[PDB]
Image (cartoon, coloured by chain):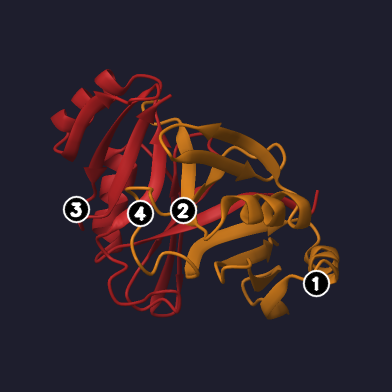
Chain colours: A orange, B red
Amino acid sequence: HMISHIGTIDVFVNDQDKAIDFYVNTLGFELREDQAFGPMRWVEVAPAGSQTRIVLCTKHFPVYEEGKIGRFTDIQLVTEDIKATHEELVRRGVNFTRAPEQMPFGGANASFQDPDGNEFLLLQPS
Amino acid sequence: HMISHIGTIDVFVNDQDKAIDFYVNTLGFELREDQAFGPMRWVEVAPAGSQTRIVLCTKHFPVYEEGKIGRFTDIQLVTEDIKATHEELVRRGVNFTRAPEQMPFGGANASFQDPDGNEFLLLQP
Protein backbone atom coordinates (compact mmCIF):
# COMPACT_ATOMS: atom_id res chain seq x y z
CA HIS A 1 0.00 0.00 0.00
CA MET A 2 0.92 3.67 -0.38
CA ILE A 3 2.19 3.94 3.22
CA SER A 4 3.58 0.52 4.15
CA HIS A 5 4.40 1.12 7.83
CA ILE A 6 5.82 3.35 10.57
CA GLY A 7 9.55 3.21 10.02
CA THR A 8 10.93 5.03 13.02
CA ILE A 9 10.13 7.05 16.16
CA ASP A 10 12.67 9.49 17.66
CA VAL A 11 13.87 9.21 21.27
CA PHE A 12 16.25 11.93 22.44
CA VAL A 13 19.27 11.09 24.58
CA ASN A 14 22.27 12.88 26.16
CA ASP A 15 24.89 10.37 24.96
CA GLN A 16 24.37 7.88 22.11
CA ASP A 17 27.06 5.46 23.36
CA LYS A 18 25.53 5.30 26.82
CA ALA A 19 22.05 4.94 25.27
CA ILE A 20 23.20 2.16 22.91
CA ASP A 21 24.53 0.39 26.01
CA PHE A 22 21.20 0.85 27.80
CA TYR A 23 18.85 -0.06 24.92
CA VAL A 24 20.90 -3.02 23.63
CA ASN A 25 22.58 -4.52 26.71
CA THR A 26 19.95 -3.83 29.39
CA LEU A 27 16.65 -3.72 27.43
CA GLY A 28 17.85 -6.41 24.97
CA PHE A 29 17.17 -4.49 21.73
CA GLU A 30 19.16 -5.08 18.54
CA LEU A 31 21.52 -2.36 17.33
CA ARG A 32 20.06 -1.74 13.88
CA GLU A 33 22.05 1.23 12.59
CA ASP A 34 25.16 3.14 13.67
CA GLN A 35 26.40 5.27 10.81
CA ALA A 36 28.31 8.58 10.78
CA PHE A 37 27.08 11.36 8.47
CA GLY A 38 27.76 15.06 9.26
CA PRO A 39 29.11 15.48 12.73
CA MET A 40 25.77 13.61 13.26
CA ARG A 41 25.51 9.86 13.93
CA TRP A 42 22.36 7.89 12.97
CA VAL A 43 21.66 5.31 15.66
CA GLU A 44 18.71 2.90 15.52
CA VAL A 45 17.69 0.24 18.02
CA ALA A 46 14.73 -2.09 18.00
CA PRO A 47 13.29 -5.12 19.66
CA ALA A 48 14.59 -8.23 17.93
CA GLY A 49 12.60 -8.97 14.77
CA SER A 50 10.29 -5.93 15.23
CA GLN A 51 9.32 -3.72 12.32
CA THR A 52 9.43 -0.12 13.70
CA ARG A 53 12.74 1.16 15.10
CA ILE A 54 13.66 3.82 17.66
CA VAL A 55 16.15 6.44 16.40
CA LEU A 56 18.37 7.60 19.25
CA CYS A 57 18.70 11.31 18.62
CA THR A 58 20.98 13.80 20.29
CA LYS A 59 20.92 17.46 19.69
CA HIS A 60 22.61 18.57 16.57
CA PHE A 61 19.50 16.69 15.19
CA PRO A 62 17.18 19.30 13.52
CA VAL A 63 14.31 17.18 14.86
CA TYR A 64 15.28 18.02 18.55
CA GLU A 65 13.74 20.66 20.81
CA GLU A 66 14.54 21.65 24.38
CA GLY A 67 12.43 19.45 26.69
CA LYS A 68 12.64 16.39 24.37
CA ILE A 69 15.32 14.56 26.43
CA GLY A 70 13.77 12.82 29.44
CA ARG A 71 10.01 13.07 28.77
CA PHE A 72 7.13 10.60 28.50
CA THR A 73 7.78 9.12 25.06
CA ASP A 74 4.13 8.09 24.40
CA ILE A 75 5.58 4.70 23.27
CA GLN A 76 4.11 1.42 24.45
CA LEU A 77 6.41 -1.58 24.38
CA VAL A 78 4.94 -5.08 24.24
CA THR A 79 6.13 -8.13 26.25
CA GLU A 80 4.63 -11.63 26.40
CA ASP A 81 5.65 -11.91 30.12
CA ILE A 82 5.52 -8.62 32.03
CA LYS A 83 6.27 -10.40 35.34
CA ALA A 84 9.48 -11.90 34.00
CA THR A 85 10.48 -8.80 32.05
CA HIS A 86 9.85 -6.49 35.06
CA GLU A 87 11.93 -8.75 37.31
CA GLU A 88 14.79 -9.01 34.83
CA LEU A 89 14.91 -5.27 34.02
CA VAL A 90 14.80 -4.33 37.75
CA ARG A 91 17.66 -6.79 38.31
CA ARG A 92 19.62 -4.90 35.58
CA GLY A 93 18.99 -1.56 37.36
CA VAL A 94 15.98 -0.23 35.42
CA ASN A 95 13.85 2.39 37.16
CA PHE A 96 10.16 1.52 37.15
CA THR A 97 7.90 4.50 37.83
CA ARG A 98 4.98 2.06 38.00
CA ALA A 99 5.09 -1.67 38.75
CA PRO A 100 3.03 -4.22 36.79
CA GLU A 101 -0.67 -3.66 37.34
CA GLN A 102 -3.56 -5.68 36.05
CA MET A 103 -5.88 -3.72 33.86
CA PRO A 104 -9.64 -3.68 33.49
CA PHE A 105 -8.75 -3.46 29.90
CA GLY A 106 -7.31 -7.02 30.33
CA GLY A 107 -3.60 -7.82 30.46
CA ALA A 108 -1.23 -5.71 32.51
CA ASN A 109 0.97 -2.65 32.18
CA ALA A 110 3.83 -0.85 33.81
CA SER A 111 6.07 2.18 33.21
CA PHE A 112 9.84 2.54 33.25
CA GLN A 113 12.50 5.03 32.30
CA ASP A 114 15.80 5.01 30.53
CA PRO A 115 18.83 6.72 32.13
CA ASP A 116 17.77 10.13 30.74
CA GLY A 117 14.25 9.81 32.24
CA ASN A 118 12.62 8.92 28.88
CA GLU A 119 9.52 7.05 30.04
CA PHE A 120 7.95 4.04 28.30
CA LEU A 121 4.78 2.06 28.85
CA LEU A 122 5.27 -1.70 29.07
CA LEU A 123 2.30 -3.85 28.16
CA GLN A 124 1.37 -7.52 28.27
CA PRO A 125 -1.79 -7.64 26.11
CA SER A 126 -4.90 -9.72 26.92
CA HIS B 1 13.50 -11.77 24.02
CA MET B 2 11.86 -9.78 26.80
CA ILE B 3 10.44 -6.97 24.67
CA SER B 4 8.95 -8.22 21.41
CA HIS B 5 8.04 -4.90 19.68
CA ILE B 6 6.70 -1.35 19.84
CA GLY B 7 2.95 -1.85 20.14
CA THR B 8 1.69 1.74 19.93
CA ILE B 9 2.60 5.43 19.64
CA ASP B 10 0.22 8.19 20.76
CA VAL B 11 -0.87 10.95 18.42
CA PHE B 12 -3.11 13.67 19.93
CA VAL B 13 -6.11 14.99 18.03
CA ASN B 14 -9.02 17.47 18.54
CA ASP B 15 -11.79 15.27 17.12
CA GLN B 16 -11.47 11.50 16.76
CA ASP B 17 -14.20 11.27 14.05
CA LYS B 18 -12.28 13.67 11.92
CA ALA B 19 -8.91 12.09 12.68
CA ILE B 20 -10.34 8.64 11.77
CA ASP B 21 -11.52 10.12 8.49
CA PHE B 22 -8.00 11.48 7.81
CA TYR B 23 -5.88 8.46 8.86
CA VAL B 24 -8.27 5.75 7.59
CA ASN B 25 -9.87 7.30 4.54
CA THR B 26 -7.24 9.83 3.31
CA LEU B 27 -4.00 8.05 4.34
CA GLY B 28 -5.41 4.59 3.62
CA PHE B 29 -4.71 3.23 7.15
CA GLU B 30 -6.72 0.45 8.72
CA LEU B 31 -9.02 1.28 11.61
CA ARG B 32 -7.63 -1.27 14.12
CA GLU B 33 -9.71 -0.29 17.20
CA ASP B 34 -12.73 1.88 17.93
CA GLN B 35 -14.20 1.23 21.43
CA ALA B 36 -16.07 3.52 23.83
CA PHE B 37 -15.04 3.24 27.49
CA GLY B 38 -17.22 5.81 29.24
CA PRO B 39 -16.46 9.37 28.15
CA MET B 40 -13.25 8.19 26.40
CA ARG B 41 -12.92 6.43 23.08
CA TRP B 42 -10.05 4.02 22.34
CA VAL B 43 -9.11 4.52 18.67
CA GLU B 44 -6.20 2.83 16.88
CA VAL B 45 -5.10 3.23 13.28
CA ALA B 46 -2.26 1.62 11.33
CA PRO B 47 -0.94 1.00 7.83
CA ALA B 48 -2.20 -2.30 6.39
CA GLY B 49 -0.20 -5.26 7.65
CA SER B 50 1.99 -3.06 9.86
CA GLN B 51 2.96 -4.06 13.38
CA THR B 52 2.98 -0.75 15.35
CA ARG B 53 -0.29 1.21 15.65
CA ILE B 54 -1.08 4.87 16.30
CA VAL B 55 -3.46 5.48 19.20
CA LEU B 56 -5.54 8.55 18.42
CA CYS B 57 -5.72 10.31 21.77
CA THR B 58 -7.57 13.41 23.04
CA LYS B 59 -7.08 16.23 25.54
CA HIS B 60 -8.93 14.13 28.15
CA PHE B 61 -6.49 11.15 28.16
CA PRO B 62 -4.16 10.85 31.21
CA VAL B 63 -1.14 10.77 28.82
CA TYR B 64 -2.05 14.26 27.44
CA GLU B 65 -0.08 17.43 28.26
CA GLU B 66 -0.48 21.02 27.05
CA GLY B 67 0.94 21.34 23.52
CA LYS B 68 0.81 17.65 22.46
CA ILE B 69 -1.91 18.38 19.80
CA GLY B 70 -0.47 19.71 16.52
CA ARG B 71 3.25 19.10 16.81
CA PHE B 72 5.99 17.30 14.99
CA THR B 73 5.22 13.71 15.92
CA ASP B 74 8.80 12.40 15.52
CA ILE B 75 7.29 9.63 13.32
CA GLN B 76 8.74 8.62 9.92
CA LEU B 77 6.24 6.82 7.72
CA VAL B 78 7.65 4.57 5.00
CA THR B 79 6.54 4.47 1.35
CA GLU B 80 8.06 2.56 -1.58
CA ASP B 81 7.25 5.40 -4.03
CA ILE B 82 7.28 8.87 -2.55
CA LYS B 83 6.49 10.55 -5.96
CA ALA B 84 3.31 8.48 -6.36
CA THR B 85 2.38 8.77 -2.68
CA HIS B 86 3.00 12.52 -2.56
CA GLU B 87 0.86 13.12 -5.68
CA GLU B 88 -1.97 10.84 -4.51
CA LEU B 89 -2.05 12.44 -1.07
CA VAL B 90 -1.98 15.90 -2.59
CA ARG B 91 -5.01 14.84 -4.75
CA ARG B 92 -6.79 13.84 -1.57
CA GLY B 93 -6.23 17.28 -0.01
CA VAL B 94 -3.24 16.50 2.21
CA ASN B 95 -1.17 19.57 3.10
CA PHE B 96 2.54 18.96 2.58
CA THR B 97 4.84 21.28 4.60
CA ARG B 98 7.79 19.96 2.53
CA ALA B 99 7.71 18.38 -0.94
CA PRO B 100 9.78 15.27 -1.63
CA GLU B 101 13.51 15.95 -1.89
CA GLN B 102 16.61 13.78 -2.17
CA MET B 103 18.39 13.50 1.19
CA PRO B 104 22.14 14.33 1.44
CA PHE B 105 22.87 10.78 2.61
CA GLY B 106 20.50 8.68 0.50
CA GLY B 107 16.73 8.26 0.21
CA ALA B 108 14.03 10.86 -0.25
CA ASN B 109 11.63 12.44 2.18
CA ALA B 110 8.82 14.90 2.64
CA SER B 111 6.67 16.10 5.50
CA PHE B 112 2.92 16.52 5.83
CA GLN B 113 0.38 17.40 8.46
CA ASP B 114 -2.96 15.95 9.61
CA PRO B 115 -5.98 18.35 10.07
CA ASP B 116 -4.82 19.29 13.60
CA GLY B 117 -1.28 20.15 12.40
CA ASN B 118 0.37 16.91 13.62
CA GLU B 119 3.42 16.59 11.38
CA PHE B 120 4.92 13.40 9.97
CA LEU B 121 8.01 12.62 7.97
CA LEU B 122 7.40 10.50 4.89
CA LEU B 123 10.39 8.49 3.67
CA GLN B 124 11.25 6.45 0.58
CA PRO B 125 14.30 4.54 1.83
- Crowding at mark 3 (Cα within 10 Å: few <14, some 14-19, many 20+): some
**Contact, mark 3 vs mark 1 (Cβ under 8 Å):** no
Q: CA distance from mark 2 to mark 1?
A: 26 Å
Eyeballing the image, is B71 above or below A100?
above
Residue A80, labelled with which disc? none
Depth order, front residue of B58/B120: B120
| Amino acid at the residue labelled 1 | Val
* Side of A64 relative to A99 (left or right): left
x then y, percent, for residue B101: 24, 25
Secondary structure at numbered mark 4 = strand
| Amino acid at the residue labelled 3 | Pro
Residue at image mark 4: B73
| Amino acid at the residue labelled 2 | Thr
At a point 43% along the width and 39% down the height, the residue shown is: A39
**Contact, mark 4 vs mark 2 (Cβ under 8 Å):** no
- Crowding at mark 4 (Cα within 10 Å: few <14, some 14-19, many 20+): many
Q: CA distance from mark 3 to mark 1?
A: 41 Å
Front disc: 4 or 1 = 1
Residue at image mark 1: A90
